Length: 315
Ligand SMILES: [Mg+2]
Ligand SMILES: [Mg+2]
Image (cartoon, rainbow, N blue to C red; front, top):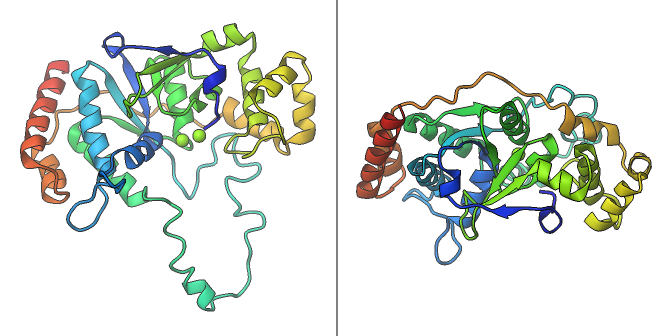
């Protein structure tokens, strides 16, 4: 996401100081994280005997239990319906290139079949099936999840602002742009220590408003305007913001500036979800993990036993 890291205040926090907090996990960010970091010695992903990747299932299972063991109650947040994701104020223009220039012409020729074998790949190793399988596993584990109307980071941020959860868990800083009061990094990955970023601290320290921060992100470049504004990094953007000339510059330099701003300010969110935990289906977990995905029975068994006890106590 936006490379805010070096320019915003952040603090290393211990796992103990995270004890008892409820958090909204950015599901897609977490799953991509697992695929990247849960690999073999040769950098190859974890797979079952059928050659299917299980890296994501490994992180979902073990990472979720790790948090619960430390009294951190997670609620997984996933992205909305790929076909339709227009988030309340997110339909005016596009969510891709469907409406506008996407090219309609007869080209079924070989270049279309080598291509008709060239569409299921850029969806990375994280396929809808895999994402669906992760949702299934969370269900068996008794862990609550929400399917956001659109971007999961907006849903999670909303949940944090509401106070249903203490922070958004992700490796990206982007939740701050949606008004998330707190983001906690390095929980799904522990190379480095957990890192807590508080939005209010960032704003007070930099002496800027949330709208200013969104402006800086747009200069740098968001998923909605990759590459940002020609030759402008954090410092120059922050300079333009403090001078009070950012909004004029952005209106000139970024088409759909007002549209991009609305995405962060008025996303489509939902209140239909529960943070309640359910006792885990031990047998179904073992079938899916051990039987169908070749996880080690012993380790899995000890873990579903631990999971059940934790939830029971919590419940
Ligand atoms: Mg992002
Ligand atoms: Mg996202």
